[PDB]
Image (cartoon, coloured by chain):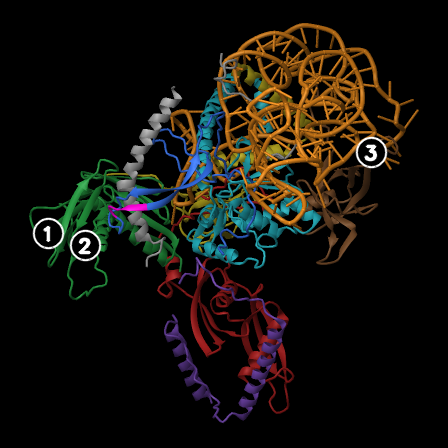
Chain colours: A yellow, B brown, C green, E purple, F red, G cyan, H blue, I orange
RNA sequence: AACGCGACGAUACUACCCGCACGUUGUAGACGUAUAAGAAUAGGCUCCGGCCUCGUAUCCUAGCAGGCGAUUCCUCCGCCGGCCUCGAAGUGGCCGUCGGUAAUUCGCGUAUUGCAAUUUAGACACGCGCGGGAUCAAAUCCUUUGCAGACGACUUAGAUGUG
């Protein structure tokens, strides 16, 4: 019996999955309330990634690929924090590509006017090198 | 070889007047600024200058370019469209037309 | 009521190979190859064990899960067609005018043409073209009978219905004139 | 009576067109084509093989 | 029916002012007639109505009913 | 409807020589504000007992809030609603964080499913189901099913409504 | 992002007729030049027999005495159907409306002037973003063909040719992008350690 | 009369145009479709009829025929057409 | 379609085409008017490493409105030719020549428009001028014809010929 299926690979909502909010924050699911709302908590020590324990809608939520392995259902703030530092959620979020793009966006937005000329000039230098490299091939 | 642009204004489009369902008031015009989407973006440009630049048939003092000056007064609605007051009401043929929004007076 | 999960399962024989694309299903086996598009129904195809495929609907209705029972039986029918095939035995009867059935296969378009002559004395020839992949024969095991076999149950059944409909009596007494070609037996080749 | 646009009448006409008139017209067409065929045979840029440009609008003028 | 290939005359939903006035007037007339018939009322009326009570699907019907019973007992013994 | 909170009201008939120290009736209700709370309390007391607004006073009105607004609870609401046929009973179940949220969802659902309005709906008893085996409705049963995990297929991306034109066709997968 | 362009080309495939017409009419009256392509690939919500019934009623509506002048000219082409929607949404009986309609252009398929240009999309009118998955939809091209549009096959053949040429262009794009990737890493060393880390710190 | 030919109007051109050529497929041999001629008049003939099933089968039937003088045509051009969404 | 379109022949004047001097010439309205896969959305892309909410992306973007001169650079751009390519309402590539060209750094000029006043600067279309090539036409009226006809209109014929 040979079966070859390539249909989908979604990300599921369950207890222990951390998800990203439009403030840019992270919160782990503690209890699933309905099919479109969950209860979440962010105990992260980083003030940018901290999220108060409360109800979040999945419409506002965004699913990240990090899942706490055995986070108990209904875990209160102290225990979800214990699991957070046990699993090192901050390091893996930093390693993920979404946070990298967010940081690049933040740098580009906070980049001032002198800095905008500097970037233009340095990209021109890199562009000259890249064109020299591309001319050979 | 500068090969670069020389723009110092923000593009805008005169859309219509401040009007009701029937009655239209040519005193104040509605301006859609390029890139403004919300009332905070509008609040940045409150008070800025606006000029409608058009071409005429006769050159009076060295040019055929005539300009009507005004200022952005207040935001309009929730989509970033602003209300503008000009020294003269706009020709009402310039609905959907271009205006230049100048950054002075500056506060940043 | 928006059921969160509903799952269905289809088992597969050892000697078959199922290749399923976005929603194209292709099945290969000893008898041949059958392909069908199911892109009109929302389903997630999955593997749960070595020799069983899975069909699921999340956040669906009773209409959605009813589609999942139809999607299974259709795929199961295709698997059975590629393993054992399908066969319809039909019989033609008459009272006074023998029904003459001529079956041939044209090189062009690769289809089977069945010609019916002398249906209650009519001078018109009735030509029916089969769906591709259907073999039609006049077997010498019983008289006045025809066998229509193939890989696709839908094609075989539609062909049998086509002959049955083309041999229909008009403006007569149904209780008195008993002539036609009728499906007698339904089953598998193996 | 059956109309000139009847499906069965159209099927009969198709059979007639495929069985008799088809062959007859094909034969006459072959003969006339042979006769007319007999009557008939009774650098890229400076050669023309490279097809180039000779000698309202769809796009908005920029 | 061949409605798709050969549609018939549409039925206008555009309400006329003559119709709106007539329907409002007849609605008011029906309401007044209902009020007059209710004034007439050749029918009996009782005080206590048939209360359907707690549904059998209530998870705490037993607790609520025993609460009620002990309430009756207490009221009877106190009064 | 609106934003609600628990309002517990004690009111009593105005003291007289004949009957000093009256009964001090009390009940808990759902109102957007204290004025509506007192009006509903007086309406219900007029309907139940022979006490009216003029011959009564409001001893106390306090806001009851939730003991634990952070833990997910299942609520059973027994309610009576009057439609064109008459008064009918319903027990319905809601999975929320508060009795306030349960009552909000109940008004919304009754309006959506039966077109019953605020004065057409009576809240007879709202309870918190102390444990499973007290849930009788299949949707909340499937919500409390063990090891519940589900995907969110066909997620329409949230694009700005002022972004009229896009350069790429959006995806509905994540 | 509320951007003003000279002319914007809208790919009509997978777009709801009325919603796309609303967006296009608002843009035209604000002063933006619109070019809609693949009007035969446009979509209409509901089911095909409902759309065909509506169009047959439209055909039923006709002037008695003289069909030549004053009568409703029943245009059968999908571009003309979309134009009818946009005209019904624009005050065409005014000079302003006439100017907006002169700013509008519509075509069937993608003509060679517009095949090498960028085609934008309107997410506020897309079928896959708007309709519920279980709901039916029909094709404006199919409706036009069943009402009497004579050039479905010609447009189909031209689209096939355009898609083949686009596949060739995309193979060339693959070659160019692969060479660009190789060129970037090859001069990743030959540059200046400062510039590189400088760009990384500044977000590039 | 017939609403097919009505509004009745003078022909825009004296020559008269074909308006429809027979559908073309590559399998058939190469041939021309139409021709020109000048009407000369009509005459009477008789025909040894060979129409089966008719009352005049194997009999002589007098029929009226028309004569069109057809001098040979001279070819002076070649026109190439293309298919577009507009026709 | 008499305010829809295509192909072709001949186009005297006028000026048909070519280059710039431009125009106190027009434009429901330039100011970087930059950006081609297709297809699916209960899936897709790929260099086959992996990647995909996110066009808040990529390209381009410095220099008297962008001057002059150097060290250094072989990168970008445009005009002409050659070979081919593009017909759905018709273009792009390769090669070549020729002209321009901050990827690094420096020098000599900018002042005075006086504390802002559209930074008159783009494209297509049209018109006057020169100096280079070239062309050297028809229709209507009139007479006639009758395949036509209320009147117009239409089919015909008038330049040395089968008039």
Q: In this view, does G121 lie above or below I57?
A: below
Q: Does the magenta stretch include residue A113?
A: no
Check disc 1 and report the residue beneath it. C144
Task: Decide whether the magenta segment is chiefly helix, strand or loop.
Answer: loop
Relative side of G161 to I92, left or right: left
Q: Do the dots labelled 2 and 1 sit on one chain?
A: yes
The region drawn magenta spans: H57-61
Could you give the CA–CA distance between mark 3 and mark 2, rounded to whole angstroms? 93 Å
Determine the CA span between mark 3 and mark 1.
Answer: 99 Å
Q: In this view, does C103 lie to the left or right of A106?
A: left
Q: Name the residue under label 3.
A: B64
Q: Do the residues labelled 3 and 1 touch (CB within 8 Å)?
A: no
Closest to the observer: D30 or G72? D30
Question: In front here: F134 or I3?
Answer: I3
Secondary structure state at the residue bearing disc 3: loop
Provide residue B6's location: percent of width, then percent of height: 73, 28
Q: Nearer the viewer, mark 3 or mark 1?
A: 1
Subunit that carries the residue with mark 1: C
Which chain hosts label 3? B
* Nearest to the observer: residue A66 or residue G24: G24
Q: In which quarter of the image is residue F75?
A: bottom left
Residue A112 image-quadrant placement: top right
Mark 3–mark 2 contact, CB under 8 Å? Answer: no
Residue position marked by numbered label 2 in the rendering: C122
């Amino acid at each position: 019996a040979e079966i070859n299926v390539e249909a989908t690979s979604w990300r599921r909502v369950e207890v222990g999955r951390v998800l990203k909010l439009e403030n840019g924050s992270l919160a782990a699911i503690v209890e699933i309330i309905d099919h479109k709302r969950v209860l979440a908590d962010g105990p992260s020590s980083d003030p940018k990634l901290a999220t108060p324990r409360g109800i979040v809608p999945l419409s506002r939520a965004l699913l990240t690929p990090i899942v706490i392995p055995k986070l108990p259902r209904g875990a209160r703030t102290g225990a979800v924090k214990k699991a957070w530092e046990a699993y090192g959620v901050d390091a893996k979020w930093k390693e993920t590509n979404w946070a990298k793009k967010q940081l690049q966006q933040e740098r580009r937005q906070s980049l001032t006017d002198f800095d905008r000329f500097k970037v233009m000039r340095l990209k021109k230098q890199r562009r000259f090198e890249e064109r020299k490299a591309l001319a050979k091939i | 070889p500068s090969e670069a642009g020389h723009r110092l204004y923000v593009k805008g489009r005169h859309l219509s007047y401040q009007r009701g369902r029937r009655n239209t008031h040519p005193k104040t015009s509605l301006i859609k600024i390029e890139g403004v989407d919300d009332t905070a973006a509008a609040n940045f440009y409150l008070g800025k200058r606006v000029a409608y630049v058009y071409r005429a048939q006769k050159e009076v003092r060295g040019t055929k370019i005539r300009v009507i000056w005004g200022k952005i007064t207040r935001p309009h609605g929730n989509s970033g469209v602003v209300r503008a007051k000009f020294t003269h009401p706009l020709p009402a043929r310039s609905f959907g037309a271009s205006v230049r929004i100048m950054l002075y007076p500056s506060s940043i | 009521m928006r059921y969160i999960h509903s799952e269905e399962t289809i088992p597969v024989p050892e000697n078959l190979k199922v290749s399923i694309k976005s929603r194209l299903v292709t099945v290969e086996g000893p008898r041949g190859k059958l392909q069908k598009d199911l892109s009109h129904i929302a389903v997630n195809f999955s593997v749960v064990k070595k020799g069983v495929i899975g069909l699921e609907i999340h956040h669906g209705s009773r209409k959605d899960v009813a589609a999942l029972r139809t999607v299974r039986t259709i795929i199961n029918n295709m698997i059975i067609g590629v393993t054992k095939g399908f066969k319809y035995k039909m019989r033609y009867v008459y009272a006074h005018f023998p029904i003459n059935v001529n079956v041939e296969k044209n090189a062009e378009t690769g289809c089977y043409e069945v010609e019916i002559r002398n249906f209650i004395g009519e001078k018109i020839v009735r030509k029916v073209v089969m769906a591709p992949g259907v073999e039609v024969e006049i077997s010498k095991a019983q008289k006045d009978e025809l066998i229509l076999s193939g890989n696709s149950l839908e094609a075989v059944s539609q062909s049998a219905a086509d002959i049955q409909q083309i041999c229909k009596v008009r403006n007569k007494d149904i209780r008195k004139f008993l002539d036609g070609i009728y499906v007698s037996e339904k089953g598998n080749i193996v | 009576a059956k109309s000139a646009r009847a499906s069965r009448i159209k099927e009969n006409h198709q059979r007639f067109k495929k069985n008799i008139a088809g062959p007859v017209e094909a034969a006459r067409l072959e003969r006339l084509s042979a006769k007319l065929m007999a009557i008939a045979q009774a650098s890229g840029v400076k050669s023309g093989k490279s097809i180039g440009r000779k000698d309202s609008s769809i796009v908005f003028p920029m | 029916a061949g409605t798709i290939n050969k549609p018939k005359k549409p039925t206008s939903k555009r309400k006329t002012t003559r119709l709106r006035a007539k329907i409002s007037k007849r609605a008011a007339e029906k309401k007044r007639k209902e009020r007059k018939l209710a004034r007439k009322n050749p029918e009996w009326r009782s005080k206590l109505k048939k209360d359907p009570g707690i549904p059998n699907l209530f998870p705490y019907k037993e607790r609520l009913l025993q609460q009620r019973e002990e309430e009756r007992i207490r009221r009877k013994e106190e009064l | 409807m609106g934003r609600l909170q628990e309002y517990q009201v004690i009111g009593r008939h105005l003291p007289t020589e004949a009957n000093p120290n009256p009964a001090l009736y009390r009940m808990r209700i759902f109102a957007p504000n204290e004025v509506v709370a007192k009006s509903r309390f007086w309406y219900f007391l007029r309907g139940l007992k022979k006490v009216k607004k003029a011959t009564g006073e409001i001893v106390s009105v306090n806001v009851i809030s939730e003991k634990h607004p952070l833990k997910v609870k299942n609520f059973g609401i027994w309610l009576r609603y009057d439609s064109r046929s008459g008064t009918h009973n319903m027990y319905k179940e809601y999975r929320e964080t508060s009795r306030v949220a349960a009552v909000e969802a109940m008004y919304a659902d009754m309006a959506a499913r039966h077109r019953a309005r605020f004065r057409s709906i009576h809240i007879l008893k709202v309870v918190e189901l102390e444990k499973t085996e007290d849930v009788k409705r299949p949707y909340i049963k499937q919500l409390v099913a063990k090891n519940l995990s589900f995907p969110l297929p066909h997620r329409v991306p949230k694009i700005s409504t002022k972004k009229i034109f896009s350069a790429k066709r959006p995806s509905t997968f994540s | 992002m509320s951007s003003f362009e000279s002319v914007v080309v809208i790919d009509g495939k997978g777009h709801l007729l009325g919603r796309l017409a609303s967006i296009v009419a608002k843009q035209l009256l604000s002063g933006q030049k619109i070019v809609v392509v693949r009007c035969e690939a446009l979509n209409i919500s509901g089911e095909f027999f409902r759309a065909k019934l509506k169009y047959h009623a439209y055909l039923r509506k006709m002037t008695r005495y003289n069909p030549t002048r004053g009568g409703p000219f029943h245009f059968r082409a999908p571009s003309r159907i979309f134009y009818k929607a946009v005209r019904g949404m624009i005050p065409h009986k005014t000079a302003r409306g006439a100017a907006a309609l002169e700013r509008l252009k519509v075509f069937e398929g993608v003509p060679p002037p517009y095949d090498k240009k960028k085609k934008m999309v309107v997410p506020q009118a897309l079928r896959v973003l708007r309709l519920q998955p279980g709901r039916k939809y029909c094709t404006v091209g199919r409706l036009s063909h069943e009402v009497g549009w004579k050039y479905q096959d010609v447009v189909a053949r031209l689209e096939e040719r355009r898609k083949a040429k686009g596949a060739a262009y995309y193979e060339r794009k693959k070659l160019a992008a692969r060479q660009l990737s190789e060129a970037k890493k090859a001069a990743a060393a030959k540059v200046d350690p400062k510039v590189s880390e400088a760009l990384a710190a500044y977000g590039y | 009369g017939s609403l097919a030919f009505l509004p009745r109007k003078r022909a825009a051109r004296h020559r008269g145009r074909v308006k429809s050529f027979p559908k073309d497929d590559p399998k058939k041999p190469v041939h021309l479709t139409a021709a020109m001629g000048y009407k000369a008049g009509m005459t009477t003939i008789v025909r040894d009829l060979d129409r089966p099933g008719a009352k005049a089968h194997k009999k002589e039937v007098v029929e009226a025929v028309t004569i069109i003088d057809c001098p040979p045509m001279v070819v002076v051009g070649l026109v190439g057409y293309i298919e577009t969404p507009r026709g």
